[PDB]
Amino acid sequence: QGLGCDEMLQGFAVAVKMGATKAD
Image (cartoon, rainbow, N blue to C red):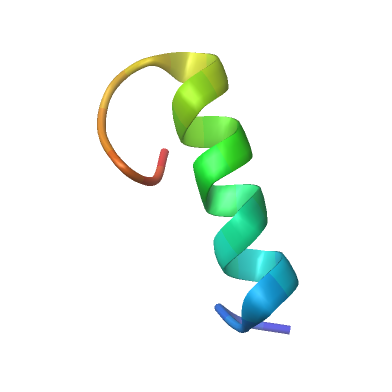
């Protein structure tokens, strides 16, 4: 995996959970 549909989605889930940018 890298940054497809689920990987990019996880980048937003971790970013919104951390609170820094679009992907954290």
